[PDB]
């Protein structure tokens, strides 16, 4: 359920999976980091 | 006399030839990291460009001495006067 307001609790369903100018320095590898960030993001939306 | 003059032409070719070889390799190593810095920090390229010229004067310090001596040997050979 989503907290629309103090009087409204909207039941809802949303898709967890599947989902400027300059660029970042990557340590150790970009692929290594993308795999780690995506799990942290799904476990975050579930806790939310 | 011919051996002094002939070997002087080769001394001249070694002075500027080794200088050309080292400055072209040196500016490829230096310039390659300048383009990378400009790609990572595009708004900072004016600073990176100014920082690069401080190294260019040091990279060409001994090479310009070799070029100066090479021209001296060609138009005022200091060995022909040594009998």
Image (cartoon, coloured by chain):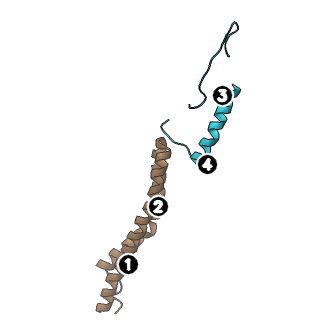
Residues tagged by mark 1 and mark 4 found on one chain of the structure: no
Q: Which quadrant would the C terminus of chain B be assigned to in this image?
A: bottom left
Q: Name the residue under label 1.
A: B14
Chain designation of label 2: B
Crowding around mark 4 (Cα neighbors within 10 Å: few <14, some 14 to 19, many 20+) is few
- Compared with B16, A37 (above or below) is above
Q: Name the residue under label 3.
A: A45
Tell me how far mark 3 sits from mark 1, CA to CA.
69 Å
Chain designation of label 1: B
Q: Which lettered chain is shown in cyan?
A: A
Tell me how far mark 4 sits from mark 3, CA to CA.
25 Å
Q: Name the residue under label 4.
A: A27
Provide residue B81's location: percent of width, then percent of height: 33, 88
Provide residue A24's location: percent of width, then percent of height: 55, 43
Chain designation of label 3: A
Q: Residue at x 59, y 41 (%)?
A: A34
Tell me how far mark 2 sits from mark 3, CA to CA.
47 Å
Q: Nearer the viewer, mark 1 or mark 4?
A: 4
Q: Which of marks 1 and 2 is in front?
A: 2
Residue B72 location, quadrant: bottom left
């Amino acid at each position: 359920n989503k907290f629309v307001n103090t009087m409204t609790q909207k039941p809802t369903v949303e898709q967890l999976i599947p989902l400027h100018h300059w660029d970042y320095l990557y340590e150790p590898d970009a692929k290594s980091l993308l795999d780690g960030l995506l799990v942290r993001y799904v476990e975050s939306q579930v806790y939310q | 006399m011919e051996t002094v003059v002939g070997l002087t032409a080769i001394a001249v070719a070694l002075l500027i030839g080794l200088g050309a070889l080292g400055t072209a390799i040196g500016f490829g190593l230096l310039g390659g990291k300048f383009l990378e810095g400009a790609a990572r920090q595009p708004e900072m390229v004016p600073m990176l460009q100014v920082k690069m010229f401080i190294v260019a004067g040091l990279l060409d310090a001994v090479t310009m001495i070799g070029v100066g001596i090479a021209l001296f040997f060609t138009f005022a050979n200091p060995f022909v006067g040594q009998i």
